[PDB]
Amino acid sequence: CDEMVHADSKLVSCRQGSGNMKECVTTGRALLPAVNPGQEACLHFTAPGSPD
Amino acid sequence: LCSSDSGTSSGLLPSDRVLWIGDVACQPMTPIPEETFLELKSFSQSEFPDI
Figure 1: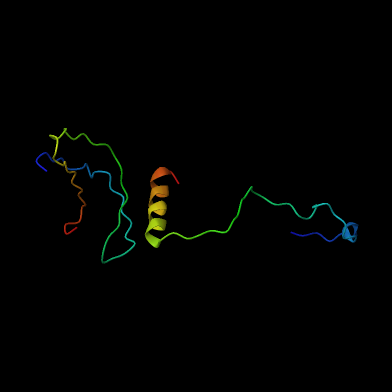
Figure 2: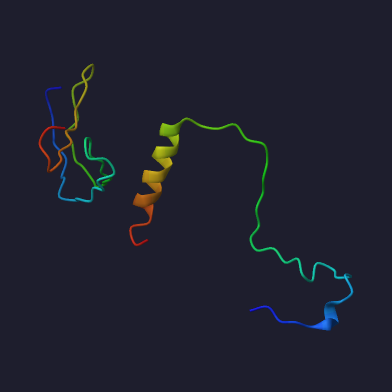
């Protein structure tokens, strides 16, 4: 993807059901520009924790 | 608290002692994978922010 927009992860509510791998549930709204035909557009997800 | 009384000595009662809450339908069922269950659990959380 050439055009890419990340989420707005400021909505934070994650329950630590497992310690090795975390869990979280979130929602919101997004505004990504239209990509050219024949190509795919992305959407990045972020968490306060680093690795995943 | 349950209360003793002889007025119920006769066993005849038109569902007087049998009152059922709710309106439930039941049937034989085929299960779903465990992950499909996990999808419903999370989605229910989102829809009721207050609960």
